[PDB]
Length: 173
Length: 173
Image (cartoon, rainbow over the protein chains, first blue to last red):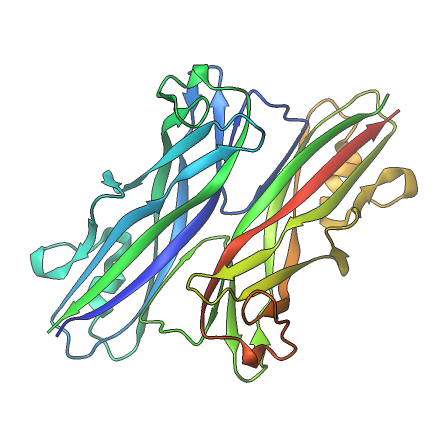
């Protein structure tokens, strides 16, 4: 039978619209979105991750996929306003409804920066690699229900929440 | 009248005890605590942050404090097991019940690695500096209510939660 493993990677995220910037404090690695009056929208953020796997010495193929679990940021006050964070892996969406292929040795995918996993999955020891996702704001609500993509219509304030991505590894023999 | 500003810095945190590590994925900058049988407890980790302030040309003193807001990690399963994360700044606890002084120019506390802020607070530019807190596991429960003394008594699994710290800046003249 296949060997399978799962891990969930969670980033904390904040977004700000029209708030004071007299004091800004940012944990390293955190996803920080800022509404820009300039372009009427939010910046994107690259968020990096480290992966480690244990080798399966008799495996003959390896697959690594990702799937979005949570992505909702909510304002800190009484507004109920939310933002949803889109996640991209090398130009391909990582969504809640499917598994985005990152490595698939059988079908001709190495995973780019994740290539060490594609080469080490059937070593007898552990293999490590580092890559990232691009995170962006893909929708929002004024109040938790009324959805928008015109972000100029959002109430001012701060949103926060966790963005969690599930990773699924499969070793085949 | 003095000028004040506030910001909340949030880290995503995960703790693990005796779980399978066939696949491990770790967002950069996230807090990660691993139980080790040898020490009967978890590692600590220094989590870094950047602080940016806007100058106030009329000010004659500056103060920056921190206060812990949330620090509870909860297991992902039905256990109800919790861990609480302690936060230290240069050997002084940052707690939920008071404000820990980081900079206080009126009293010659310049802020160590944050000292550029003490120098630039009344300048007419943005000043940025970096520092960190040491994060550690300071308490835990087996089930949400039973306090443990010996971490070896914890149920196996993964705890996750956000650790959030409020920063407060005051410019006086």
